Structure formats: C-alpha cells, structure tokens
Length: 566
Image (cartoon, rainbow, N blue to C red; front, side, top):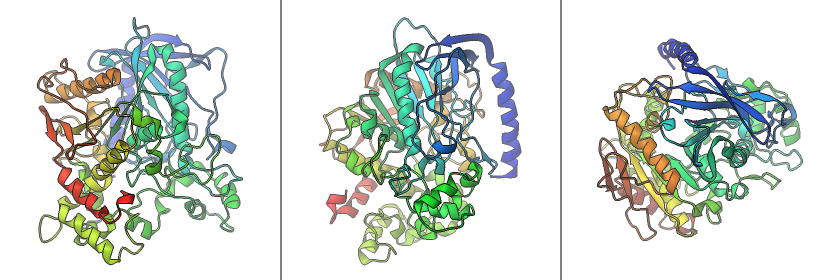
C-alpha cells in the first residue's frame, strides 16, 4: 500500500481516536454474565443516536503459551466488575495499510451493543463474524462500528477469533493435539457465550442470527454445518461466501514444516519437533512469513491461503470439521434454519489491485485451465480433459479474441463466489427439511461513502460494485461521514439494516415498512427452480432472475461426466 494512503490512514487513525473520545459519555453501566459483572459505556454516533457499548468481553482463555494452536478453553471468572469500556487488541495479522505486523495473541473477545439495556421485550440478536480471508480482520469500531444497526431495536455482537497460522495450524500426529481449525473453535465458543449471556443485555436467546461477509460468510456457514453448534442460533446470512468456496478450506498439514523452516527451524520434518519450534517462535515472526509459505504450484492451482479451515486429521473433543464441507452439508443442522445468501453485482472487481501487479494473470484465460475446479483438474493442468473444461470456462467470460482484465475479474466473480453458491444450493436441496433460502444481489454503486477495503483493492475511482462494497452500508468506519438523510447512500443504509433486522426477527426478509419494497414479492428458492430469483438492490429494489445464471450453468457443465463431484 502506497506511502500516501499510509500517512492518510495515520491521520484518520488519529482522528478516529479523538472522535471516539468525543463520542464517549460518562454513563457507565454494569451487566451480568455467567463469568461475572461487566462495565460498559454509552456512546454517540454522528447521526445523534446513542448505544450501550460493552467491549473486550473474554469468551475464552487467552490462547498463549501452551494454549497456542490449541482449541480454546473457557475463561476464568472474576469477582468484582470487569472494565469493558475499551476495545482489546486484534488477532496477530499483517496490517494491509502499513505492511507491519500488529495485534496480539490475547485476542479472544467479543463486543456487545444496543440502544436499550432494558427493553420491554426481548430483542433479536445479531452476531457478526468479520471476514479477511481468515488472516486479517477485527471487531474494532474503526472498522465495524455498530452505529447504523443501533438505530434498530436489536442487540448487535461483533466477535474476534484467531487468524492465520495461530488460528489454523494443523498437524497429522494425533499425540500433539493440534487437529486444526482452532480459529473456528473460537467462533463456536463465542456462540456458546452469546447463547448463555445475550439475555443479560436484553437479547432473545431464542432468536439469534449469525451473519458474516467473505471469510465471515464461510465462518457463518461452518457454524451452520458443524454438530458443535446445533440449535445455538436460528437464522443465517451468507454474504459473498460459504464453506465450499475454493478459498474457504485447504489441507495444510504439510505446511507447518515449511513455516517452521521460514522461521529458522533446524531439524527434520516430523510434527513434534516442528510443533516445538513453532510453539516458542515470536508470534509476529510466524505471521509475517505466512505470505511465503505457498509453493508456486499451489499459487498456480489457485490456493489462496496457506492456513485456513481444514478437514481435521483425527477427532477430538472440540472437533469442528471432521469431513469435507460438501459431506457435512448432507447432515447439517443449519440446513433447517431460515437462510439468506447473496453477492454483489461485480465481485471479482476486487482483484483489480492484484492484476495491477501481475498483468501476466490475464493470459491465464487463454485456456482458463488454472480456474478449473481443482478436484477435476490434473496436477500440471495439462490433460486434454482439463483443457476441455477450461474451454467451457473460457466461453463463459472471454468476450473477444483476447481476454481482458474485465473478463478476468468477471471470471473471478464466478470462480470465487457465484459457482460455489450454486453448488451449495443444489447440495442443500437434497438434504433439507424445506426451510426457505432467500437470495439478494447487492448492486448499489457509490463513491460518496466508502470503507477501508477499497484502499486495499485499490478501488479508488473505480466504477462497479465490488466484493466488500456493501459493508459500508452496514457498519460505520473511520472513513465514513454523516450523510444527508435524503441521500441515496443514507436510504441504502436504512434498507440494508432494515432487511437484515427484519430477516433476523422473522426468518423472512420482506417488510412493507422498508422504503422501496412496496412492489417487492421476495420468494425463496425452490429445488424445482431452474433459474434463481433474487432481490436486486440498487437505487431501486427489484426482483429479477439472477443475471449470473447462464455462466453459472456453463461452469456446472464442466461436471457433465462427473456428476458425483458436483
């Protein structure tokens, strides 16, 4: 990231701190939790609303020392009153702005928000799991501010969880108790905390909604797939992702060794000796070198991250993913709760920045063999069947004689987002009680209000609605500003938070009390549907057939001779 966005972000960081002090009140309050009493503070928003803020609530023991890479344990209760008037640190991660490593291993907290600590009726509880490829993200309010949501009468909860190698190291050897998915196991225990404690904040423990975007969407889906969370919540929202996205899981058991070797390990490739080195390495050293772990073959085969959610090698007490996600959908308790899914109208536009560094990537679309689903493609991507499959992809996105960056970014939309959504919907249909799934398409383009991901994707002055453009209309961030109430952006905030709270409440996203929705007939998706219908969200709200459907079926035809793998 540029030296200009570095000084610019440095300034907004200083501004966000003064604004946050300014927006604090003297009104402290205490709430009960099963671990003891917590002290929150009332805060202000730039729209002159206010909310109770409880930050730095521990939901697990700090995963330090011998607990590093291990499943989380319950925290230690306390007498007295724990101070929750400040945020704790984020998980150790590489700062996308500076490139420096920041964060702390002591990161396993959640934040609770609401405009009314003593509502006259129990409220819907909405749990947000942030994205960031399982390697970045946080629940800090400079990024995920609760300011738009607390205009509504809900309780909003933002959780953190271990990221990167510290979140997702995985070793085969059953003696060392590092099966994998530590970071997901963090999310589970946070759900168990929210279940047993939301009531103390005016929340309804019987009406809980978990949602998230990108890696947070994959997370949300995982919480809907695993047995560990059965019955914990009642609605799910999958925003631009799910667990069968190709980036949402990986077999990384061999990569521990490589990481150790990058960090200076001397010795042989066995898990024990590998683990012992990793256990005493400085945390920021491990995180900083994660970028180097993937081999060039793996990057070629479109492996996006070295460490992430994985099929655990053996089953233990807190196991989360005992089988590949496709297999888990077949028995998942979550198939039988109300579900909303969606994507933006130009997902792959996010990859503008990557192409800017590697224009050689656009040539991958000459045969598209690298984007063939890996389970179908051969190692070298050279088999004639693989060239055939690649040809089908090529027909779907290469508009001319030579591929462009746009063809590329359009393909990515499908490879990373729409095709997995399709595969999940069809698998789910053959294994579900018949609970509705609703689709949305986010199509609202604006440069007048942005969020920090636009700095990373280099989305400055770029038209089209990219992956993460929607977050702007859900959460406040330190790049936001007060918007005129008649503006298209303000309306979109109102609609977006309106639809989500409505879905959270009823398991049905439609409300006539939401502006623009008066002609809307939002029907869910049925197994018999050949064509998906979705609520397309732009300056107006309109039910349409998903525009991406033709390309979606093109991809599915790659599985013509391998229907068992679809």
